[PDB]
Length: 174
Ligand SMILES: Nc1ncnc2c1ncn2[C@@H]1O[C@H](COP(=O)(O)OP(=O)(O)OP(O)(O)=S)[C@@H](O)[C@H]1O
Ligand SMILES: [Ca+2]
Ligand SMILES: [Ca+2]
Image 1 (cartoon, rainbow, N blue to C red):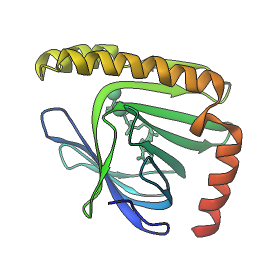
Image 2 (tube, protein in one colour):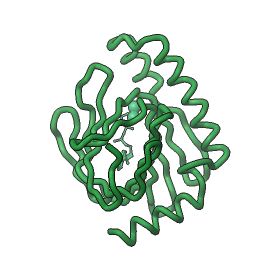
Image 3 (cartoon, helix red, strand yellow):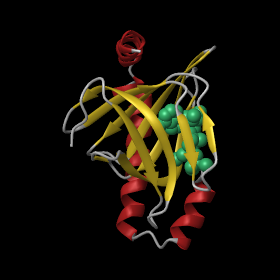
Image 4 (cartoon, helix red, strand yellow):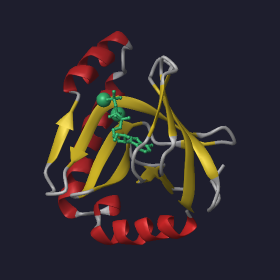
């Protein structure tokens, strides 16, 4: 169930109601442990819930954790490193894909370190429409606070040395 280094995997995101949200066709595995999966992708096909497709324009390093309710996408744009963080179930991985539930809230981090919590409106609507249990609401709000602290502390994928190591490792394997 732990992906191997050099493996190309699919990533499948779902909503709480079981519907597919988004699928990324190809991510190369850089690190696979029981707790952490790091991958890189570049010009991967992306499929939306209506089947519509688009191809990513730039490389990304992706960070998944088995014990935290978020995952982190690290983007290399012309004026520096952008992060897009999903609030989410932790991941599971099987032969089909690395899989998680998308829980609406998102955090964007700019090259200057500024972060913004996005999609409180999306979250409120979906939590009512799909009847998220109280304990999911508590865990997600706890994990928003944990993720803001990781960003402020430059912990995990927010460490500049993390970016140096994995961006170079992906450039070599690709
Ligand atoms: N797994 C991924 N691999 C590569 N790029 C990704 C990945 N996930 C997100 N991105 C990039 O991160 C940015 C935001 O991701 P989106 O696909 O917009 O996700 P999202 O923010 O969860 O959207 P909503 O709120 O569900 S419509 C875009 O630049 C994406 O290309
Ligand atoms: Ca999201
Ligand atoms: Ca969202």
